[PDB]
Length: 175
Ligand SMILES: O=Cc1cc(O)ccc1Br
Image (tube, rainbow, N blue to C red; front, side):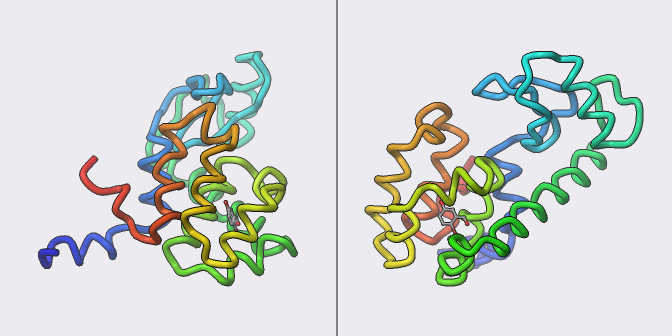
């Protein structure tokens, strides 16, 4: 690796990782599962009603947005969603011990997964959680690849699954 590539490690963190997986959109749009979304993967509501989604948006941002936000507002909402995912792992008696056993880069993949799926969805993956705590990385990844989370929307999940396999940032390189 060049001095370049050894530096890529310090450029990557959970915010840059989720930013690649979720993208950045300043107007309400439907994600791959058809849920209204905005910003960096902020799911507004699972209602098919755009009006509900606009309502959730104005609550979340605190102004009359009419479906559109700024980059700064997107980043603020993103930071809030990241903190919620972390806090949801740390208070959960099933997820915390597994998270504590992980290295720094797989801990980012765990926060990413909870950001995407929510706590109860992730904590339900009993086999994946035990494989990870036992450092059975290849099996954990194969089992994540069976999930509906990955299969209904592979492009948003694939790099998280690669990161659980390898504990490196390689899947985020060379976009
Ligand atoms: O915390 C979330 C999480 C998510 C996973 O897919 C595996 C392990 C953990 Br600890």
